[PDB]
Image (cartoon, rainbow, N blue to C red; front, side):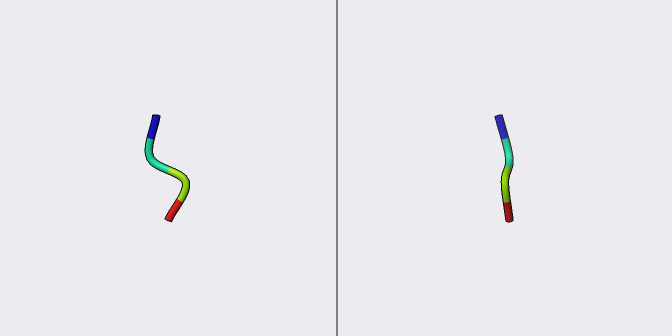
Length: 4
């Protein structure tokens, strides 16, 4: 998961 990449959220920034």
